[PDB]
Amino acid sequence: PFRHNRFSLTPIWGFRRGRDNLPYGVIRWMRDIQDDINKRASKALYILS
Amino acid sequence: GDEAMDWAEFDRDTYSQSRTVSTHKRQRVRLIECWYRKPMRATK
Amino acid sequence: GDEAMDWAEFDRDTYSQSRTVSTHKRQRVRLIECWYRKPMRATK
Amino acid sequence: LDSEEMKELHRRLRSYLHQELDRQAENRFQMAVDEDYYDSIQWTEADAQVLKERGQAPLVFN
């Protein structure tokens, strides 16, 4: 019924991947570094213990 | 087409590595718009 | 011509190391504009 | 009007498009790879496999 010829849902975009235009958030790279940080901390604690 | 846009379209087409496509499949075509300049040699 | 401009033009013409060039090909020619000075010895 | 000359024009345009595609293939590939490196994708497949055999998860600093 709406006069405007556009979808109801409006997408608030973010970083868009260049290859496929699939959106990705801020997290990805810092997630990688975070898992590395967790591995390093666990390894150091195990070596000390 | 070059590898960029063809790769994007074909990645969309393949969906997954091994997928059972149904009878209903969206069909996409390539249209190329060319703007070219040719001399006129106007008499004036 | 020196290596610079001919290198650019021949890189354009070569396309790649081995390509199947079609019958239709852009034909490019070289024109040289020479501005020279000669004394006239006007009596005045 | 398509038959008499537009077929020749279309063939000429297709030849020009092929020439400009193969001439710019190196640069097009380089720009594509630059865009891939922008979004934290910086490991080639061979060296990524080398890292995988090492037991080390590939990392991107970006």
Image (cartoon, coloured by chain):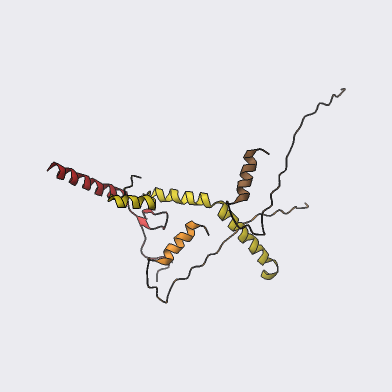
Chain colours: A red, B orange, C brown, D yellow
Which quadrant: the N terminus of chain A? bottom left
Residue A28 in view (yes/no):
no
Viewer-side residue, B29 vs A15? B29
In this image, B11 relative to B42: left or right?
Answer: left
Whether residue A37 appears in this view of the structure is yes
Q: Residue at x 62, y 42 (%)?
A: C7
Q: Is residue D10 left or right of residue D51?
A: right
In depth, the one of A28 and D21 nearer the eye is D21
**Which residue is pictured at 14% across the width and 41% down the height?**
A48
Snapshot quadrant of residue A47: top left
Q: Residue C41, image x and y in percent?
A: 85, 24
Q: Residue furthest right?
A: C43
The quarter of the image holding the C terminus of chain A is: top left
Q: Residue at x 61, y 44 (%)?
A: C8
Picture coordinates of residue C34, whole percent (x, y): 74, 36
Residue B42: horizontal and vertical position, in percent?
Answer: 75, 53
